[PDB]
Amino acid sequence: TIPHLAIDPFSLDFFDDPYPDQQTLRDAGPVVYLDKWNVYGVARYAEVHAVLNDPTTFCSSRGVGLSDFKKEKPWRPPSLILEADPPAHTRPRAVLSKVLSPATMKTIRDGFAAAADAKVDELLQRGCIDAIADLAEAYPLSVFPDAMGLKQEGREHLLPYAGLVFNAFGPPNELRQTAIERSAPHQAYVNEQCQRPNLAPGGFGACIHAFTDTGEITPDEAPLLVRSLLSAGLDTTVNGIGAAVYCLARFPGELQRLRSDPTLARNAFEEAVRFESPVQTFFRTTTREVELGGAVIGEGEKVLMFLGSANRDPRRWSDPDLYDITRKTSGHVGFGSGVHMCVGQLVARLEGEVMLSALARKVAAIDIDGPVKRRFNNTLRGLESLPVKLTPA
Ligand code: HEM
Ligand SMILES: COc1ccc(/C=C/C(=O)O)cc1
Ligand SMILES: [Cl-]
């Protein structure tokens, strides 16, 4: 009773324009079977939300990529947070929640906002820039490694490592093979910086190690928790901020509404996360036979959740293909939902808000003025190059 589809959601053709295929995935049924990779798929909001919020049935400890850790060796030691179920997940989650807490945002906000304002003013002196390399990448590179407390040496490995991280959740296609092959130098750099002596006191990494005193994590758990932030904390925000600028460039009416009320910056970024869904997909693995939308899925099956499709499902969203900075976005699954919901969401929103605030106060127009190039990744959606001309307000 389950429709079988041949759509490859990790193919370059799909990445290049996923929306027609996502509708076919939604409209085929609440649950589909993807013959290309032998996994189940859910693409509607209701089922994606249900799977995310049913962690005892749809577990994370067998991996959140295609690979089943019960069957294949993980490419690196399993994540203590992303690839753990409760109760093992709980205390590492609590540490990260405290390290990336509301109280912590107060300590970094002035620096993050200052860097965003300075970057936009710098770009306005150049006129014609690449909104990826010069903005979406440059700005997070200017604040997040420092907030982590990383040394200067080796930071050139951060974006390559993240590309590997997010390609590795995918199937064994060319993107994944090429990423994992000869990835040892990227892994070695990151694993070295996770050690306590290499992390600046006061930064996120040192604060993680400081929590080993409390009994919430052991000293040998702290480097892997630092690793989780170096895996997820940079490339996500690159594609989130790039998504927002791409939206503002394509919807000039919405840039003008943002200009008229810069306090819409935070929601304008949140809507960009829904609209583009920089993190497109994650998997779960069934721990038991389970009925889901009329489908009876066996134990030990991989289930692919299309977060971006859920965020564009007209069953849930009015006018889902419209970028609307005053939309009530609560309930979107671009940061996940439930026990694994993005623990770094305050850092992501802070970066996005202060950058969009700077644009709102300083920029009158954003015009695409060069060839746009898409960046292909098994998990991340975003652009490789976005040439724009910025007109000062
Ligand atoms: C626009 C930016 C971001 C997006 C769209 C995003 C997306 C997501 C999603 C969808 C999940 C859920 C994973 C799952 O359910 O399996 C997640 C979890 C996570 N994210 Fe974020 N993320 C972003 C930024 C960040 C930042 C800035 C950090 C760290 C500074 C971070 C660190 C993490 C970690 C450690 C987890 C694992 C949480 C857990 O398993 O409990 N992410 N993210
Ligand atoms: C939202 O994407 C991600 C990606 C990776 C991770 C953790 C990685 C690790 O523990 O090494 C967490 C979230
Ligand atoms: Cl690693």
Image (tube, rainbow, N blue to C red):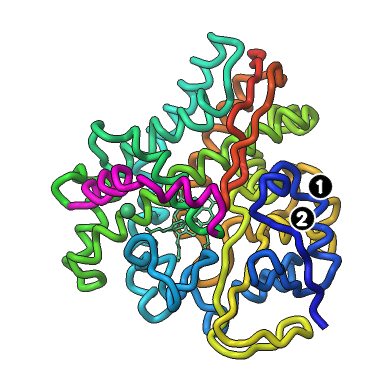
At horizontal 43% and vertical 71% (from top left) the residue drawn is 72
Q: Look at the image and tell me whether residue 247 can be seen.
A: yes
Q: Which residues are magenta?
A: 172-195
Name which quarter of the figure residue 386 lies in.
top right
The quarter of the rendered structure image containing the N terminus is: bottom right
317 or 182, which is in the foreground?
182
Q: Position of residue 211 (x, y in %)?
A: 23, 63
The quarter of the rendered structure image containing the C terminus is: top right
98 shown above or below 367 = below
| Residue under numbered circle 1 | 321
Dot 2, how many residues are within 10 Å of its Cα: few (below 14), some (14-19), or many (20+)?
many
Amino acid at circle 2: Arg
Q: Position of residue 249 (x, y in %)?
A: 71, 28
140 or 364, which is in the foreground?
140
Instruction: Tell me the SS state at disc 1.
Output: loop
Q: Residue furthest left?
A: 197
